[PDB]
Length: 288
Ligand SMILES: Cc1cc2nc3c(=O)[nH]c(=O)nc-3n(C[C@H](O)[C@H](O)[C@H](O)COP(=O)(O)O)c2cc1C
Ligand SMILES: O=c1cc(-c2ccc(O)cc2)oc2cc(O)cc(O)c12
Image 1: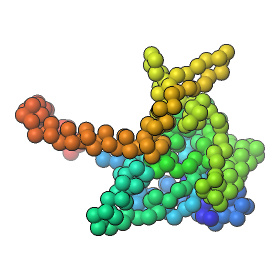
Image 2: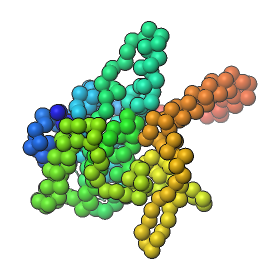
Image 3: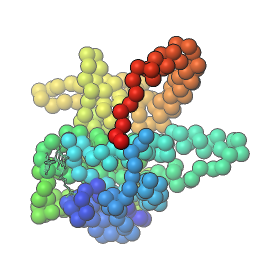
Image 4: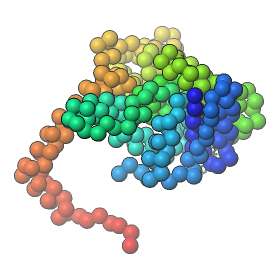
């Protein structure tokens, strides 16, 4: 099995070391290993080296991804790579687009795109402003539905490479990801159990009568039993979870419906007139 490790830090920084230490654990379990430093890549925002990167991810059986924490989440570059997964890696649309290709004599999209795959994440921050990065990491695996094995957070980690026990945790994440790639089907999540019995997430959006898992998006309720929190929801909701084929199909169907309504609305006079007034009112300032 091939384990691919990706670092989002500075060249030769702590994320490099944590991600390389994990590759070592993966080689210890008999995996072939490869390492990509994102600072060498040119990746444009979602309106260039991206297709190369995605191609490498497709050939790997498992991936370890180490990102720095910026403002209690992953880097803008991580977010960009998440943005740029949608058009290409959504398990839903690729199942659909494959079927349609078969049934209309289309050409069969890249098979690797639909292969099950395992992925692990480590978030390395310099202080404890780290409340959002795990959920960021999950988001990236949610679009292709890659089975997440570990999704660890490492606060107060400026000097982590001389803290042997945390370096060792990263070696164990390397182990886990290789063992899991040995049998992607029966691989099982190894990380924190968290609060969402489904997502494992600990991030929730809270309004009156509705708590929503920020990762998987079940709407449910959050219960405080003497300072311990838990998340319950109605078993209908599993049908809609954003990390299930069922919920993706629902989500994609509603997108196609509302994109048709949009295309029709853009031919009304209401739309055209309102747009024509906006252009008349003001023009965008650009740098000379
Ligand atoms: C713009 C910026 C924002 C950051 N925000 C956070 C943060 O919110 N919480 C945190 O622990 N660390 C934060 N850090 C520190 C980084 O996580 C740290 O520099 C990084 O893990 C270094 O990794 P490297 O050695 O791989 O480059 C931030 C750093 C920068 C440059
Ligand atoms: O090492 C750090 C560097 C920075 C940073 C980023 C930009 C600046 O002008 C000054 C500091 O923010 C941080 C925020 C944190 O929560 C933790 C850090 O280690 C850092």
